[PDB]
Length: 218
Image 1: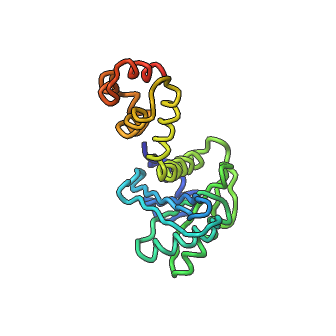
Image 2: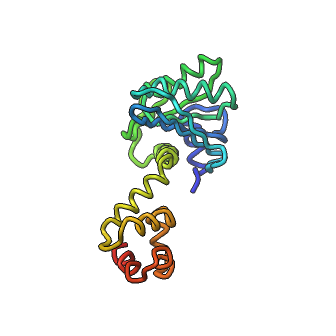
Image 3: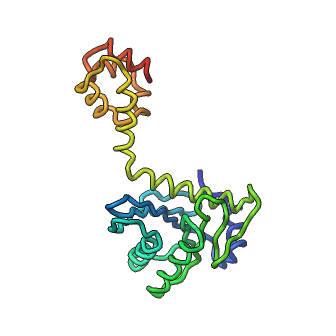
């Protein structure tokens, strides 16, 4: 799954970009209360994710300040890395403008586009553009947003997956803490254990009888 060349052309036209959006970078801002904001940065090159170029930025602050976080991210990254042809920010006029002013703060300029927080409305050049549902440019920006979100959500993936696995295993009668922990450490996630054979599960815990119950509950 990538961004269709024809939709990229349509985006180009909408934003009056003179340059084809060959590199698009997108930012999610997600705050961990009392700790730091994690900014997650994705990269599309020629419409496809370039996963090796993905990065995060951490902005230490007890309370959220998404405008400062975007500013900080833009300044940190683009003082070191080349600008993309287009920057996407997951949020509305304020977040887009925060990025633009940060770029100005370091002498830089590139087009910045947003989608207003979950309200599929395009944000560009201090304006909202309200497109019909299913407009191709809307669909394309949502795909970029979905990828920024997917990358953001993956920050806590290993811990979350173990917790979700543990929650299911808590419902297997007779399992016990030691064998529950063995399964969690061995498998890591529900997706992985759901692909295992009875025999693998039985080997991990030393009981085929309990392994059958784990299969029943899965």
